[PDB]
Image (spheres, helix red, strand yellow):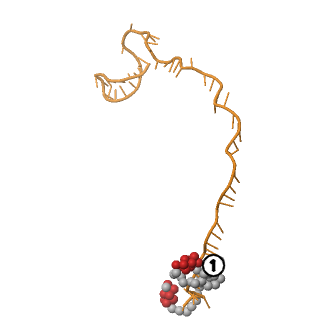
Amino acid sequence: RQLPNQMWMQTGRLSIVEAARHRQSGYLQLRAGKPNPAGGPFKTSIYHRPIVQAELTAFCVGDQQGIEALLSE
RNA sequence: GUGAACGGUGGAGCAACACCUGAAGGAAGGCUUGAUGAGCGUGUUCCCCGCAUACGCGGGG
């Protein structure tokens, strides 16, 4: 680990304003009047997962030419 | 088929209200635009310096 570990927050939110605009315009056929950030399509979820800058070292028995071909891909 | 693959940090919110840079403080004390340079004496061959190279030229008092 070249750096100390950090944590990345990412969120999943469905655009509530765009959902209401599409629901009036008819492009979204949603019969539901009220959304729910708790659960459902409009669940604004938060999830935090670790992040590391590092150098990755692995050891294996294989032909170098194919391994360098795959790793250059 | 990378414990992978998928995943918006988002929406809203006035740095604003009031506040004298001001009071006092001498540019003065002394100083001729007046002169200065404008006119007033010597009466004939005597030293010394260069170009020459003496046939003579310039020249110090």
Q: Which residue is drawn at 56% across and 83% down?
A: A30
Query: For mark 1, what is the residue?
Result: A9
**Residue B8 location in percent, x, y?**
59, 78
Name the side, left or right, on which B61 lies relative to A24. left
The chain carrying label 1 is A
Vertical placement of residue A61 versus A33, above or below: below
Residue A59 visible, this orientation:
yes
Vertical placement of residue A13 versus B3, above or below: above
Quarter of the image where the N terminus of chain A is located: bottom right
Q: In which quarter of the image is residue A19?
A: bottom right
Vertical placement of residue A46 versus B19, above or below: below
Q: Which of A44 and B36 is in front in this view?
A: A44
**Residue B16 location in percent, x, y?**
66, 57
Q: Nearer the viewer, residue B32 or B48?
A: B32
Residue A47 visible, this orientation:
no
Q: Helix, strand, or loop for circle 1?
A: strand
Please state which amino acid type lies under the numbered disc 1: Met
Name the side, left or right, on which A18 lies relative to A46. left
Name the side, left or right, on which A73 lies relative to B54. right
**Residue B33 location in percent, x, y?**
54, 20
Q: Nearer the viewer, residue A62 or B55?
A: A62
**Residue B20 location in percent, x, y?**
68, 46
Q: Which residue is drawn at 64% across and 84% down?
A: A39
Task: Specify few, some or many for label 1: CA neighbours under 10 Å numbering under 14, 14-19, or 20 or more.
Answer: few
Q: Residue at x 50, y 87 (%)?
A: A70
Q: In which quarter of the image is residue B13?
A: bottom right
Q: Which residue is drawn at 60% across and 83% down?
A: A32
